[PDB]
Every structure is written in C-alpha cells, then in structure tokens.
Amino acid sequence: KTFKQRRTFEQRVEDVRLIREQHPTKIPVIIERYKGEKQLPVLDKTKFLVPDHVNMSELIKIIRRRLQLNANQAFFLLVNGHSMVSVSTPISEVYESEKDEDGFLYMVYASQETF
Ligand SMILES: CC(=O)Nc1ccc(CN2CCOCC2)cc1
Ligand SMILES: [Cl-]
C-alpha cells in the first residue's frame, strides 16, 4: 500500500540512480498522506522531482497548491518521520542530512500536528 511496500529496496535504489542520471538538479521526494488522515485529499502521484534550490517553506506552498487547499485548511508535513526544525533550509541541504538509505527523501502530511 505505501511506496516502500509497493517497490523493493533494489527497485527504489535504481529509481533514485536514474533520477540522478536524467534529472541531476532534482531532489527525489516521496510524499504520502498520513494513513489516519480524514480532512485532506490524496495527491495525484507519489514521486516528485523538486528543484534542489527551493526551501521547505516554498515546498509547503507547492504541495498546498497541488492539493488545491484554501487558506483555513491546516497542513503539517513530516520529513524522514519528524517535524522540520526549519522551513528556511534549501532542500539540497535537507536531502543530504534527511535522505533515506534508498536515496529517496520521505515526507508525510496530515491536517493535525499529532500524526
Ligand atoms: C546514477 C548513479 O548514481 N549510479 C550509481 C551506481 C552505483 C553506485 C554505488 N557505487 C558503485 C561503485 O563504487 C562503489 C559505490 C552509486 C551510484
Ligand atoms: Cl535536472
């Protein structure tokens, strides 16, 4: 059901390697809705190629636009399983410290802080 359950470790490693070859300036990001989530919709896809210069604040704005949220819908985003310490960090720096061993950066979103 989740991305890690659908694709083998070997398969995830090879897809990150192909994104390095074909989209060298992009961060490979997995974005999934929290399994408990009621309010927010699901995304149109799972795997996202994020320009490596954007910061976490801008990525949140990007995901809010993709979900077509309105101003008063709450949105919380975990990176590698935990809260972001700072939204100002360039995603290239976030990737180097928070990437999975498969080479993806994993994110989860919910309408509540308590996931
Ligand atoms: C596109 C891409 O990133 N490819 C890739 C392929 C293999 C590795 C693993 N290497 C093998 C040779 O040296 C030891 C570690 C890393 C990256
Ligand atoms: Cl690129």
Image (cartoon, grey):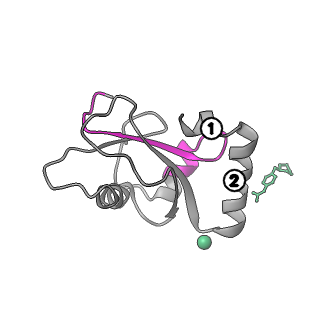
Instruction: Note whether 8 is above or below 86 in the view shown.
Output: above
- Residue 45: x percent and y percent? 48, 53
Mark 1 or 2: the one toward you: 1
Instruction: Note whether 9 is above or below 104 in the view shown.
Output: above
Instruction: Note whether 89 is above or below 109 in the view shown.
Output: below
Q: Is residue 82 magenta?
A: no
The yes-or-no answer for disc 2 within 8 Å of ligand 1 is: no
Q: Which residue is mark 1?
A: 6
Residue stretch in magenta: 94-114
Hey, which quadrant is residue 82 in on the image?
top left
Q: Residue at x 54, y 34 (%)?
A: 1
Query: Could you say which is closer to the camera, residue 82 or residue 36?
Result: 36
Q: Earlier in the sequence, mark 1 or mark 2?
A: 1
- Residue 91: x percent and y percent? 47, 57
- Residue 68: x percent and y percent? 27, 58
Question: SS at mark 2?
Answer: helix
**Disc number for residue 15:** 2
Q: Residue at x 66, y 61 (%)?
A: 19
